[PDB]
Each structure stands twice: as structure tokens, then as C-alpha cells.
Amino acid sequence: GPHMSYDANVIDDEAVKEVCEKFECTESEVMNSLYSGDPQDQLAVAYHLIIDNRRIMNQASE
Image 1 (tube, one colour):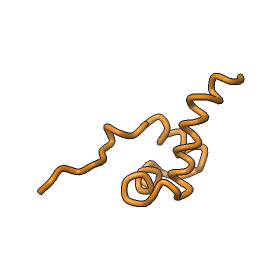
Image 2: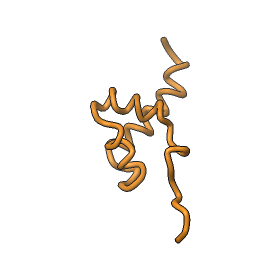
Image 3: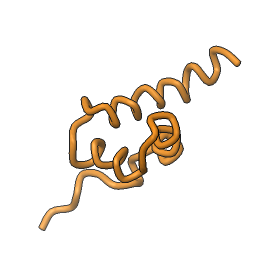
């Protein structure tokens, strides 16, 4: 059979860890909506917003 299109090599494990504490959930729940659910789910929306925070808000203020 063919190779899979996604893997932990194409996720931000620091973002997943930040979603776990900020959203109050487990890594497997964060990874599920990114791997087998859809990006519009609240756990994947948290991952997107936390990657925006980690890049921008982390530098824009202190």
C-alpha cells in the first residue's frame, strides 16, 4: 500500500504541549483533531491560535 500523508515529524510538539496546559487536555486529543478529525475543531483551533501566540504574542509583549 501507499505511504501516510501525516506524522509527528510534521507537528509542533511544543505547541501540542502548550495546547495540553492552556486548553486543559491530553496530547492524544490535540493530535486526534490534527491527524484524523478536522482543523476547524476546538483542539486544532487551539493548536493554530497557540502557534500564533508562540510566534507573535511571545515577541510583541512581556
